[PDB]
Image: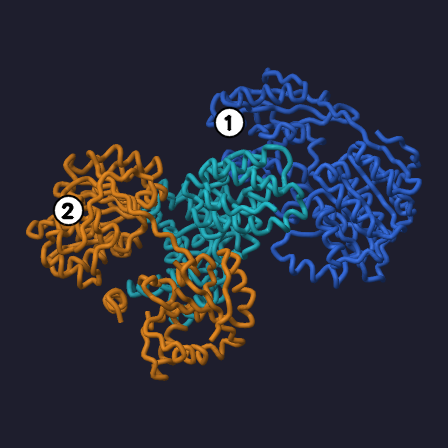
Chain colours: A cyan, B blue, C orange
Amino acid sequence: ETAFEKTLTPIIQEYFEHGDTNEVAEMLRDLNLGEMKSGVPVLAVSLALEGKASHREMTSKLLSDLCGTVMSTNDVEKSFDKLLKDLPELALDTPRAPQLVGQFIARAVGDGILCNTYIDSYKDCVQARAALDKATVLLSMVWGSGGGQQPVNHLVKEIDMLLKEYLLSGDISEAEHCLKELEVPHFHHELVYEAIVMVLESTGESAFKMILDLLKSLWKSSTITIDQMKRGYERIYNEIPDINLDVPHSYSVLERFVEECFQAGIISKQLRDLCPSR
Amino acid sequence: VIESNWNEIVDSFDDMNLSESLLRGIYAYGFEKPSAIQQRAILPCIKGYDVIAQAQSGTGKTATFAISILQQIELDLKATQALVLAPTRELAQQIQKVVMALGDYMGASCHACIGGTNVRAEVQKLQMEAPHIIVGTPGRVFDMLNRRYLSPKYIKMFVLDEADEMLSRGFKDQIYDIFQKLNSNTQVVLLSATMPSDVLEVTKKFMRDPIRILVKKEELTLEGIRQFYINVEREEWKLDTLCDLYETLTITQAVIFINTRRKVDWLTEKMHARDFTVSAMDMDQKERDVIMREFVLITTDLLARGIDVQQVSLVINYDLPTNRENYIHRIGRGGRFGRKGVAINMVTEEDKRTLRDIETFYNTSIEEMPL
Amino acid sequence: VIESNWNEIVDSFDDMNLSESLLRGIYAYGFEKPSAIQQRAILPCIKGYDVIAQAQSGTGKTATFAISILQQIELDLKATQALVLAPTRELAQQIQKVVMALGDYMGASCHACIGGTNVRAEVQKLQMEAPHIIVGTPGRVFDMLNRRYLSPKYIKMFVLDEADEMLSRGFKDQIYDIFQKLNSNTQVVLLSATMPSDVLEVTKKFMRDPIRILVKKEELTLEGIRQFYINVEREEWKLDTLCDLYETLTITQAVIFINTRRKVDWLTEKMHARDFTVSAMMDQKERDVIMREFRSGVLITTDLLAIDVQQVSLVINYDLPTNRENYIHRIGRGVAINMVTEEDKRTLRDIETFYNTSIEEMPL
């Protein structure tokens, strides 16, 4: 039994890293799990509960792409009954384990891997009700995602709106929290590159200001590692003879900007140093 | 502004003898009757005259030259036939979205330029080969004629869009240089929001007896809309006030504006929690609905132009537009000629100053929420 | 970040007057000279000061408070004396593995919490009785002080690890509530990757004249690493190319990465079949490959469990990381070699623009 977890735990976990709905599904088949099948979504969710959002997402999809291949409608029925059993026990190691489990159920029902009026026919303990009210409201109305093994130019879409939205919200934390949520901390030059472009492409003074502020406060929240910040400017110091095709002026601007940056200390006298001109 | 010398009006897109495919496209796209400019400019273009249209920034206006470049394209000939210039990558891009949209049931081939991560790939496309319609900035385009990725040989329609803009972005030289590479034969359409000397003198040196359409039209002034501010000291007490309002006006249609996607989802689901069913916006099909079934809604602000707020009696600014210009885009709309209703501002202590600015920006008065 | 107010450096573990049994245990674990952090934070701890170390995520950051809680335990007194807090069960669990590891030749008794299939059995242990060192999440731990399965009476060392993490997992409340249960006497160590207001104000409300150690952060960087891709049309011809490479570079240390355990087993035993002895990867049977790689002696691991790869001159991606972020975790920080298929063609050009980096073809 406890010989169970000692076994699945390390494929569920391995999976959060190859991301293969499949490979998982094979290896379980060959373990020929019994009734104790319904103990696999429990293990999976409850692990992802201590993972990132990624893993949370990844799991919900594993719960789908596993149900009808190697798992009965009726495992998932109970697997969820156990998750509400253990909610008081789970919240010890994940405080928001209630609302979270809730979002799992919302989606569960949604991928149709779960019964329709399930919640309804589940009618002692705030923790489960709490977690059923989540699922309820969610439905009557992602986890969003998701980073890492996402498609590259998908990430770009996100970074784009991140920036686009910021320019109308004027909300810096708001930006940070989405850059942060994407989970691709080695891709942040994209954020920087995209952002410099907006300044390069804009007219009038707001773009420039608003992006120099965001880029300072990002550098300052150690959110943009000094390395990132540099692959950023290099991408720009690079494309500028091409960008100059869509924006004449782009030169005497991007350098006016590198100047603001240097002056604000976000970049070395030697990046500022390395800027092009003609 | 320019002196109009042509205004013959065409009521329906049906009387323009457009391809049927083109027709089907322009209805699927959502158009019904042709707009101000469409009733006046499409025909002249289609008929081949140089046209100089002084009109407000496109909807609409874009659809105009788009409909005529498409009506004129020789589907059969695989070589780039109409060349359109915009002031930004962004803006060239939307032009090509509209073209492809209307161009949907015809084999029309259209391409905007960039930009530049895979320019290598962009270029190998362009020749060869060979989009029928290419849109891009004057700089990009010209650099392309120079390199010969693009042939002027078959280009028979040359449209300059937002010329005032293009010139002032620094493109005068590149515009001329392109001119002198296109056939003395090429039709020229120049639309521009405004007609400064610069623009004029382009018109003056490149167009034959052109026809001058001037269906622009201004003000534009929120005198059909009662504007209020209800004072909520802290943002904490915003959600609270909202639902209080919801039952003391019990409105059945209202659009509530929010500054970020995240805060929409927040509010949306904090209100479903309270029994007030409400919609949030995001992709076209799942989106198309909310806009298809709209055509209580909480949207960002950005997609606000993805839905017509003018047939909505109540607009509520939960957040306040950081961009002043952008306020009117949310709330107002002038008075008949339609039209509208009222809109309500939730201002914080902090927001105190920020609203008094909106108030002098549009020389307008915003009174406090009554009873 | 935090302002350093203490940096005296200790070269050898020998000069820290650690127990000899503790000493034997830290050498046996693989350590040689003390790392950045170790030369700076061990003494202060051992000497009893509240210490607040801002340092990167543990390897031997873990070994640090581990070594000083063990140096301070009263082996003779059977009651739980040092309490350590981590942000996940997973992470508490490795802490106790490190502790047991170093603590091996002393009677040190250490336990992490869970989790819960046999919590019944976990509790009846805890008291009574009564581990010297207990590690666990702030939530679990506090729930156990409340139930009285755990006594604060003898706890004299209270270490909060990855505080920035814990706080943001939602544990601020359970952290304070524990504090107010431990003696006003308890030494406090808080290590944290980052030092946001939240974290600071904990430091500010629980520590006496605390010491601040800093430790400069070591960013991964594919800067000193030559990256190659050798083109192998089909995966069929992968194993083949591997062994060709094995003799045309005859490397003596190298890590080869694979995407699944199963395909590790495959490759390992298809290579032993070929006379190329080579290692594949549970803590004791594992601890070896990590104990013996660590102090030193071809390794083919998944990716998940991916040992300090930085002291390895050659990395080879047999499989390509499905998670782009995860690439730098394998290779970078040189050289490293990519085996790309026809299919994998596109997949690599992505890695290349992800980290704004260039990957050239295998030369001669």
Residue C318's image quarter?
Answer: bottom left
Q: Residues within 10 Å of mark 1 (few under 14, many from 20)?
A: some
**Which element is circle 1 on?**
helix
Q: Position of residue B133 (x, y in %)?
A: 78, 54
Residue C172 or C322: which is nearer the viewer?
C322
Q: Is residue C111 left or right of residue A90?
A: left
Which chain is mark 2 on? Answer: C
User: Total of numbered circles in the picture?
Assistant: 2
**Which element is circle 2 on?**
helix
Label annotation for residue B238: 1
Residue C161 or B292: which is nearer the viewer?
C161
For the point 85% across and 33% down, the residue is: B214
Q: Position of residue C112 (x, y in %)?
A: 23, 53
Label annotation for residue C46: 2
Of discs 2 and 1, which sits in the foreground? 2
- The kind of residue tagged 1 is Lys
Q: Is residue B319 left or right of residue B225?
A: left
Q: Residues within 10 Å of mark 2 (few under 14, many from 20)?
A: some
Q: Position of residue B354 (x, y in %)?
A: 56, 23
For the point 89% across and 36% down, the residue is: B212
- The kind of residue tagged 2 is Ile
